[PDB]
Amino acid sequence: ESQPDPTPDELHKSSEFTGTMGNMKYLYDDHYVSATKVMSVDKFLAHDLIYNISDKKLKNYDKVKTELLNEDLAKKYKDEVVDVYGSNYYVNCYFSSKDNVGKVTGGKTCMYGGITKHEGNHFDNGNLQNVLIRVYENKRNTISFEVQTDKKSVTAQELDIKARNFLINKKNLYEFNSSPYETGYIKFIENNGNTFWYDMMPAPGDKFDQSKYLMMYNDNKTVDSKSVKIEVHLTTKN
Ligand SMILES: [Zn+2]
Image 1 (tube, helix red, strand yellow):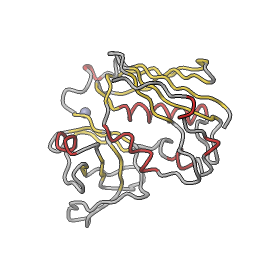
Image 2: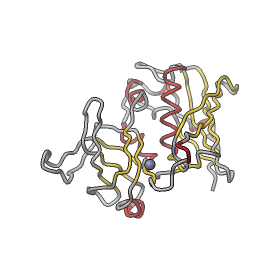
Image 3: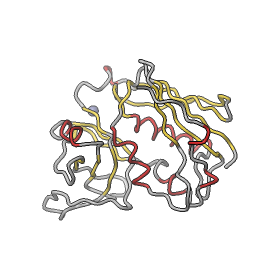
Image 4: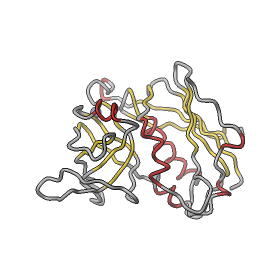
């Protein structure tokens, strides 16, 4: 059911990552795909969905492929009108898409999960929900800040992205060469008592695989924005 807290020895240490921390920072520093009321237009593999989504800013892509945990999830959202929000990558992003006139199999950008039904998923009076993030540095709550979302059921991915974007800016969570923190995990606590956490640091070694890291979001896990509680736990060292 609930996921047990990290054992001391299982959390990734920034000390053991000899690659460039900027590759991790890239995924969260004002970086995300956002789309409203779209419907998939194609598939590549059985568990993914392809959408016609182009970025106004920079014009880096016109097609987005999102991979889900399995075929049932893909099937569930295939013909649904959804909203999209997630962290995209280009390295090792593959797909032969159903490209309209202007393009030919436009394999532009990739991501995982990040899908929520549009209909009935928004607050009345067009209000935004504020979600509080409490951050602990070396076991002490140093700061707390709020992120906002207009979705009632929001992906954990969306809140994680917003939380890290703020921390990168205010706490230098990730820098180009390294990070001022040794370990770090973001923990979600749901209203029914269920808990889960994501390790915020890259796996040991000299290489960082963006697609491998973001794959954790393929479960398309959603939480109730009005009741979730989020805690960021960081230890200093680096
Ligand atoms: Zn919507």
